[PDB]
Image: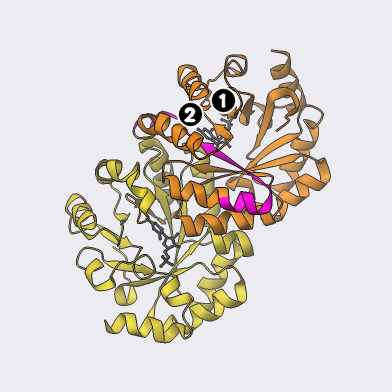
Chain colours: A orange, B yellow
Amino acid sequence: MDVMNRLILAMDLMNRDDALRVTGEVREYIDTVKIGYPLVLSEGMDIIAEFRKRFGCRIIADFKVADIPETNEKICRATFKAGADAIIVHGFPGADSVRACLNVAEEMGREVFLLTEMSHPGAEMFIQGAADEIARMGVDLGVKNYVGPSTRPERLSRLREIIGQDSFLISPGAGAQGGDPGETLRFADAAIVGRSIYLADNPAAAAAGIIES
Amino acid sequence: VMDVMNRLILAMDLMNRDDALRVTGEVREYIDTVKIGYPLVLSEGMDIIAEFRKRFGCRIIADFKVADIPETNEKICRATFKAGADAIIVHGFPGADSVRACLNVAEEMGREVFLLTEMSHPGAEMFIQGAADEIARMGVDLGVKNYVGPSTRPERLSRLREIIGQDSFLISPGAGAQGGDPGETLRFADAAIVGRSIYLADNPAAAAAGIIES
Ligand SMILES: O=c1cc(O)n([C@@H]2O[C@H](COP(=O)(O)O)[C@@H](O)[C@H]2O)c(=O)[nH]1
Ligand SMILES: O=c1cc(O)n([C@@H]2O[C@H](COP(=O)(O)O)[C@@H](O)[C@H]2O)c(=O)[nH]1
């Protein structure tokens, strides 16, 4: 995959007008946008095709898919039908749940990103202890795209070693959650940034500043 | 605690409105509580929740397996309750702060959180099962009153019940298609969730009727 400026916008605004306007403003700086459930559940899945058509951007659907295989398949199918280029899936529910997603991505010519460890404090309770094994499970299944935490650079480093130099790694937690984009890009191929941009008085200037740093 | 007709909850995972509405209507004499997940909601829109409530007067549990950071979890729950969901299902594996974020919105809006503690599919054994008892205890310690556990593992279901106590409400999927037995499940769970065994049946009402008979 090819990503402008190693910066991915997390568009978690919950009304269409704001989300489109803000994404528009930073569109000279980004060609890849992560859209999650806050926006999709508020405005409908049709919002994905709207972003793609208005901006010509790649869309990663951050749905943290975490169900049984059968339901995971349905979720991925509906999501790819709506135009998503990729979908983010949790690894914690195990290999069968991940493979169900890989199957649909294969069928429809799209991509799965495997989420291995999360960035928030609660992640240390159960996810962190499982993270290396989750990443290894992904590698062994031919997963090529991964998500790991900006907030824990040493953890981000280990993930990189596990997945190797040929895998693609994106990383949220930069900005609002305390992660540094520069430090994050020592290990990750792109940094995901949400509030620091979309809550900014001038999102273009916020994006501009991140890129300069 | 809430009240559920026939200890049977319909998992409505059909992905078009027409079919989902028709099938639900036909088993409606047997059920006042319907679980709606992302297969239907992403295909037909969140407005489908209020549609079920108005057409059938049923309770709706939004099975969204919420599994994000606290800030995002809060937004997901807000959007979901705004759309009329009576309850939302949340994963416990992302930890306590992510669960509490959901509990906060549920408190605010006067709705309910169900905590998913162990899952029913084979892959659940890789990571979730090892953590399931602690996830359940985490829920209890936070005042969670509503839980989801697996029909496919009665002995695991039995352990969950011990942890959460006799006053907690426990619902359980994996009955039917995944191999769980509704009868055995209700030794420990207050209600059994059933999807395909009903909605994929030639005669949905007959299928539901048969399950209730057993
Ligand atoms: O480990 C995780 C995985 C996520 O996808 N996310 C997500 O990435 C985004 C981060 O946004 P923000 O920059 O405002 O902190 C959100 O949309 C969020 O749900 C997270 O913050 N940490
Ligand atoms: O541990 C889990 C948790 C779930 O909510 N579910 C869900 O409950 C349902 C089961 O449907 P079915 O009876 O067709 O197997 C689905 O909607 C599914 O996503 C599961 O089967 N096992």
Disc 2 under 8 Å from ligand 1? The reply is yes
Q: Position of residue B150 (x, y in %)?
A: 31, 58
Q: Is residue A205 above or below residue B158?
A: above
The residue sitting at 36% across, 71% down in the picture is B176
In the rendered image, the quadrant that contains the N terminus of chain B is bottom left
Binning the other alpha carbons within 10 Å of mark 1 as few (below 14), some (14 to 19) or many (20 upward) gives few
Of the image marks 1 and 2, the number of the one nearer the N terminus: 2
Circle 2: residue type: Ser
Q: Tell which subunit mark 1 falls on.
A: A
Label 1 SS: loop
The residue carrying mark 2 is A119
* Residue neighbourhood size for the residue with mark 2, other residues' Cα within 10 Å, grouped as few (<14), some (14–19), many (≥20): many
Q: Which residues are magenta?
A: A103-125
Drawn side of residue A115 relative to residue B127, left or right:
right
Discs 1, 2 touching: Cβ within 8 Å: no
Instruction: In the rendered view, tell whether residue A125 sits above or below residue A39.
Output: above
Mark 1 is on which residue type?
Ala
